[PDB]
Length: 30
Ligand SMILES: [Zn+2]
Figure 1 (cartoon, rainbow, N blue to C red):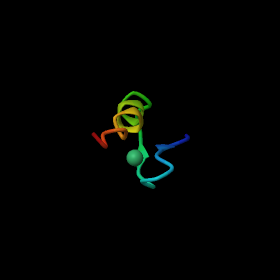
Figure 2: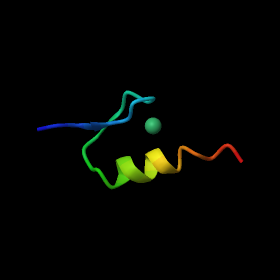
Figure 3: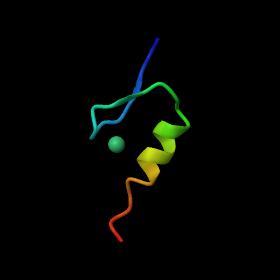
């Protein structure tokens, strides 16, 4: 078991897919 957590969020995603979208769409400054 290894939680796919976000380095900035501290939130553990149990799925690499949504942890992926969440990490790439984190780039929503504009
Ligand atoms: Zn995040």
